[PDB]
Image (tube, rainbow, N blue to C red; front, top):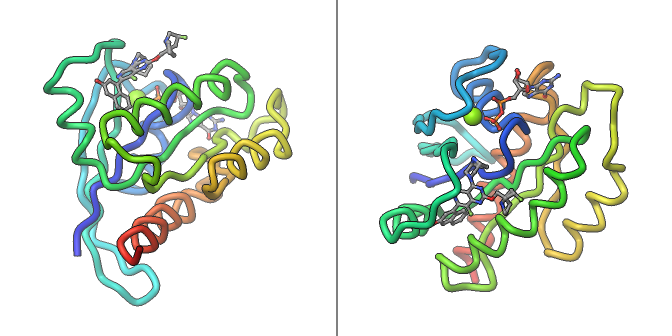
Length: 168
Ligand SMILES: Oc1cc(-c2ncc3c(N4C[C@H]5CC[C@@H](C4)N5)nc(OC[C@]45CCCN4C[C@@H](F)C5)nc3c2F)c2ccccc2c1
Ligand SMILES: Nc1nc2c(ncn2[C@@H]2O[C@H](COP(=O)(O)OP(=O)(O)O)[C@@H](O)[C@H]2O)c(=O)[nH]1
Ligand SMILES: [Mg+2]
């Protein structure tokens, strides 16, 4: 089994740091903000061996046809914001609508991720994030790429959401 996972969200929220924790087991400071890359990892989740193919998105805000078709191959999406950046939380709606648009579907596996939970300078309350996730009908996972809090949980929860979708 293989799952195509895509990590989206505003610049600086920790998409690259979360991905590199999952894949390479270390915390990277100031990874080049412009680099989009992909990684594969073999995991066991609830007894099922699978390959996670993870796209760590980056780059300019552009909407080419090639970009839509490429994003459309994603089976599940992490919607990442940082808990110290209210604008990144406000931007979650945008990324969700673009995912719906390219997938031509109201039911796309997604997980809301509030990253940088190790920082004291919080501006987005856990209750606001839980309420947003409830409104979308998706899970909310608190993470820190720095301490590895919630990292496996975020990705594995997204796989569980894909499996639920495939059962419908
Ligand atoms: O063809 C596509 C294209 C995208 C797509 N690709 C890149 C985006 C992009 N950048 C890339 C990364 C992340 C931030 C920065 C620029 N570096 N930024 C935004 O939005 C940014 C905000 C919020 C809205 C207005 N702008 C201005 C400010 F407010 C902030 N959206 C993007 C975006 F939708 C798709 C995304 C998901 C599903 C299918 C897609 C299909
Ligand atoms: N304290 C803390 N810093 C983080 C966390 N995740 C990312 N960072 C830092 O925030 C900055 C932006 O992270 P990055 O992974 O490049 O974000 P991206 O633009 O979403 O790929 C970098 O300096 C990271 O080291 C986190 O969970 N906690
Ligand atoms: Mg990055």
